[PDB]
Amino acid sequence: KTKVTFWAAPNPTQVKYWDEMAKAYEKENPDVTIEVSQMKESPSSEATIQSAIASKTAPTMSENINRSFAAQLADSKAIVPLNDVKGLDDVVKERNMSETMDSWKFSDGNQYVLPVYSNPILFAWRLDTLKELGYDAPPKTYSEALEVGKKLKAKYPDKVLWAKGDLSDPTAWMRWFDFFPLYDAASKGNAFVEDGKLVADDKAGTELLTFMSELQKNKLLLASKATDPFETGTSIMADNGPWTFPNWDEKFPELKYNENYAITAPLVPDSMVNEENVATYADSKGVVMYAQATDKEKEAAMDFLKFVYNDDKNDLKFLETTNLIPARDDATENETFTAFFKENPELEVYAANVPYSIPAMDDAKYNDIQQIIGEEAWNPIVRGEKKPTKAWSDMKKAEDGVLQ
């Protein structure tokens, strides 16, 4: 008998999902044991994993791995290429996730992670406020956003377009919720950094900063502490993930999809007013397999995943219980999910955007790389301390430093 140890995310509901999958798999394969446990945060999941590698107590597999962290683990050879474990292609094929999987491809040609969920970062809009200003739908381009903004200030001078303290904070991860969604949309998914080199789209980058400076100049940004600004009326646009809906169900029950709030892709430059399928950043994590595992343990692990993704109903169950969007390309058209999306139209918009979203960069120094984005260009523009051109150049020069 072979034993696979599986470390699930630090959340009871997600752990239960995996455990139920494990028990059903064991009924079908009596010679294999899939032991699921909830990963400890000591103080974070990443430190728990780093410590296990060091003490040689890594499990066979764990989920909860984002692309940047996977790049660190791959560089130290603590995890193995999944494409070297028989069964990977079968999993990708059956779950209809080829486009999503392809976006994860690493610089060396290997795939180190099997994405579990992929939550595109979209933007919520206050339709009620937009209607008071004469609009029936959210603007799509930077210029349209600016005209909405002028009308907003004329009727409500204390309101802003975007209110979030994180906008002026240089913490690296925060960029995944402001800069990346807009940059990915403007550059049609440019990787910013790839294969250890700065491949940033200068045009998209500088025009995004120009747009932000205009918002800043017209008092359309609020980068200070503010409680529930979007829900209480201070702002009319907010970056938003699926996890916000259960919260609104509780605290803001009057917010209703397509009545008082809308969900859309990030704003794009005017030149792309006609583009369908706008890209954004995807908050996505998945499964990796540790080098410490034997080949039989690794194949057994992949066979388990093959079992899990052989029935579309399992992804439906994942979505309905964890509220995390499954990393597949066809959810909105697949009849398995029709009834659910019919009842949850707001989640359908998220599922519709998965194949066009781009995950975090596959570079081990993502922390310094991303902190520079905020410190040198984003935070200064939000605070009106630098001009767009100078900010972008200050950023590029600093990135070169980190990348040697």
Image (spheres, rainbow, N blue to C red):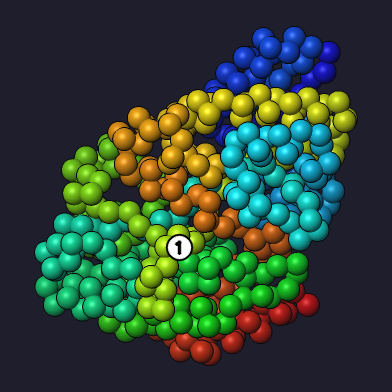
On the image, numbered disc 1 is attached to which residue?
A: 278
Asked whether the viewer can see residue 216, the reply is no
Residue for point 74% across, 16% down: 33
Looking at the image, residue 397 lies above or below residue 67: below
User: Residue 93: horizontal and vertical position, in percent?
Assistant: 65, 38
Name the residue at 52% across, 78% down. Answer: 205
Front-most of residues 167 and 257: 257
| Residue 231 picture location, percent across and down | 25, 52
Q: In which quarter of the image is the N terminus?
A: top right
Residue at 27% over, 36% down: 250
Residue 152 in sight here:
yes
Q: Which amino acid does the dot numbered 1 rest on?
A: Val
Query: Could you tell whether 94 is left or right of 316 in the image?
Result: right
Identify the element where label 1 is drawn.
loop
382 or 193: which is nearer to us? 193
Q: In this view, does 384 lie to the left or right of 76?
A: left
Asked which quadrant contains residue 148, the reply is bottom left
Q: Give left or right: position of 356 versus 21.
A: left
Q: Quadrant of residue 327?
A: top right
